[PDB]
Image (tube, rainbow over all chains, first blue to last red; front, side, top):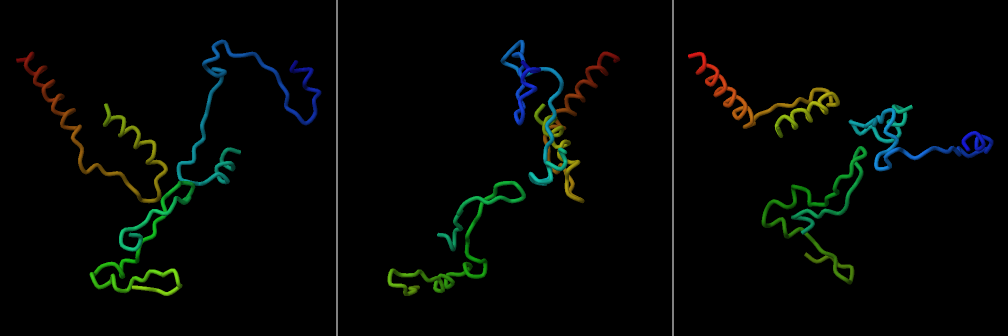
Length: 50
Length: 50
Length: 50
């Protein structure tokens, strides 16, 4: 399905399997939250994220 | 109440954080008993009454 | 355990302070609880030695 949907243009269609335990998320990799600790706002925070 | 007590109007955004907005008479004009004499409230006919 | 949590929490904000702003602890009743018990522990160990 993921390979077949790779032919769809202007749409990021991709398929995946549910996690082993749905109560949690993917539970693989890492989750990192970049935070604005000095009120830099949205515009400067996006620059930091990029 | 607004002049001598301070009225919380509504919030405002301060460096990305929501903070209150207050209206309250300047400190010079609400200190003595006689200062009440210079406060005027508009009447329905447009005149200013003390 | 609450004072430790607060002290650990305040360590997550100090890096992002504006130039010059500092944290000072002018009053805190937890050191007495910590130190006094660590004084009785000294007597407990010092009692066994005697």
